[PDB]
């Protein structure tokens, strides 16, 4: 009933649950069936955005994510049996560096959190920007600013940090 409202805070899923409730306020459905349809369309459209980010941000060697422009950075290089991973953070609340290796399963999990950040890529330069992504030391894409882009970055760094603890 309310061990639920706990599992959701306890796993950083409060943001997702909140964007869902948010999506129901904007459309204001007449029934529970209308609401659930809207949540099924919401998730489907995001899977589409994510499917397109994966096509555009496809990488063979390396990626870099650089956010809050400068003050959070992750670089990943692929290898046959493991990926290598370098992080930096210089915020007011946390300063850190990390360098270490992750499994092929870990790379797959991280890659999905990365494509999720990829949904915030802009084609403009007219627009507030939150940073960029480099692919294979060739292409560079700018990221949009704002709380949903920041949340996606938070979730991506937090997972890499978790992998640092074995
Ligand atoms: K790169």
Image (cartoon, grey):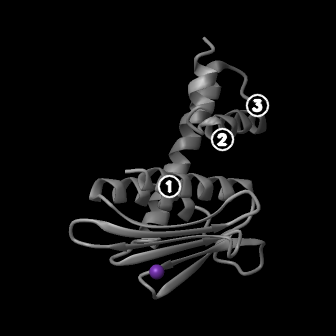
Element under disc 1: helix
Compared across the picture, whether 102 is left or right of 28 comes to left
Residue at 63%, 14% in the rendered image: 2
Task: State the residue position of label 3.
Answer: 28
Q: Position of residue 51 (x, y in %)?
A: 45, 58
| Residue 15 disc label | 2
**Residues tagged 2 and 1 counted as in contact (Cβ below 8 A):** no
How far, Cα to Cα, is label 3 from label 1? 39 Å
Task: State the residue position of label 1.
Answer: 161
Q: Is residue 104 placed above or below 58 in the rendered structure?
A: above
Nearer to us: label 3 or label 1: 1
Q: Is residue 34 placed above or below 162 in the rendered structure?
A: above
Q: Is residue 55 placed above or below 124 in the rendered structure?
A: above
Residue at 42%, 53% in the rendered image: 163
Compared across the picture, whether 83 is left or right of 117 comes to left
Q: Residue furthest bottom?
A: 138
Residue at 61%, 55% in the rendered image: 154
Q: Residues within 10 Å of mark 1 (few under 14, many from 20)?
A: few
How far, Cα to Cα, is label 2 from label 3? 20 Å
Compared across the picture, whether 50 is left or right of 150 comes to left
How far, Cα to Cα, is label 2 from label 1? 19 Å
Q: Earlier in the sequence, mark 3 or mark 1?
A: 3
Element under disc 3: loop
Q: Position of residue 132 (x, y in %)?
A: 61, 75
Q: Position of residue 97 (x, y in %)?
A: 55, 68
Q: Position of residue 78 (x, y in %)?
A: 32, 72
Q: Residues within 10 Å of mark 3 (few under 14, many from 20)?
A: few
Foreground residue, 130 or 53? 130
Q: Residue furthest left?
A: 80
Element under disc 2: helix
């Amino acid at each position: 009933d309310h061990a639920d409202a706990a599992y959701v805070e306890k796993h950083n899923l409060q943001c997702l649950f909140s964007e869902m409730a948010e999506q129901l306020s904007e459309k204001d459905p007449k029934t529970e069936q209308e609401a659930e349809r809207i949540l099924l369309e919401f998730l489907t459209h995001r899977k589409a955005e994510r499917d397109r980010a994966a096509l555009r941000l496809q990488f063979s060697h390396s990626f870099e994510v650089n956010l809050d422009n400068g003050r959070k950075i992750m670089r990943l290089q692929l290898g046959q049996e493991t990926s290598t991973l370098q992080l930096e953070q210089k915020g007011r609340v946390l300063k850190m560096d990390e360098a270490f290796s992750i499994s092929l399963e870990q790379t797959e999990e991280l890659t999905e959190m990365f494509y999720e950040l990829g949904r915030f890529v802009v084609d403009g330069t007219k627009g507030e920007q939150g940073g960029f992504i480099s692919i294979d030391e060739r292409d560079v894409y700018l990221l949009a600013a704002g709380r949903e882009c920041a949340e996606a970055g938070d979730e991506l760094f937090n997972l890499a940090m978790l992998f640092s603890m074995d």
